[PDB]
Image 1: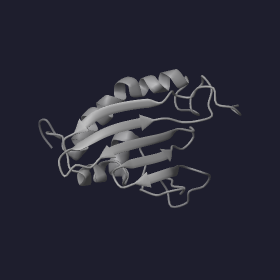
Image 2: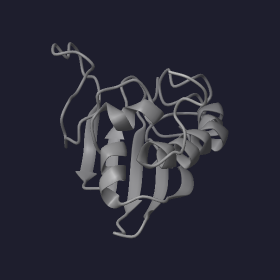
Image 3: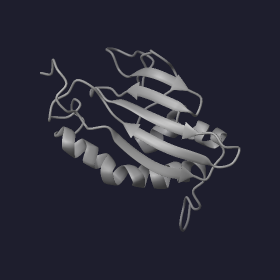
Length: 152
């Protein structure tokens, strides 16, 4: 499959300024499924070298955090793909400067591992939709403006 690292998704960085305090991003990135909401259906918990799955019985190896640091650094690898997806946060009692990293090691020109198909396309997913999600929604989850644009 993949013994050596050929490509995977090339180190993907997405940058946005979250006009928020570190604490709301805290709620939004290295945290419970609130971060998962923009990322992908999960109950991420800021854990290190753990295994976590959307159920009490984890079953096999689900997801595992490489390293986690209170809205400063988040690194964890998601489910089936070998992506060491990392979140980089700037603490300002001021607003929060967000640098997002989606990276992973030991995959070919094929993706991280059922991430989509091509390692290139998956980085492309982040290359458009990830500013939508992180640049627009990470600022949204930490702040947004409207949630139900008409009625609820």
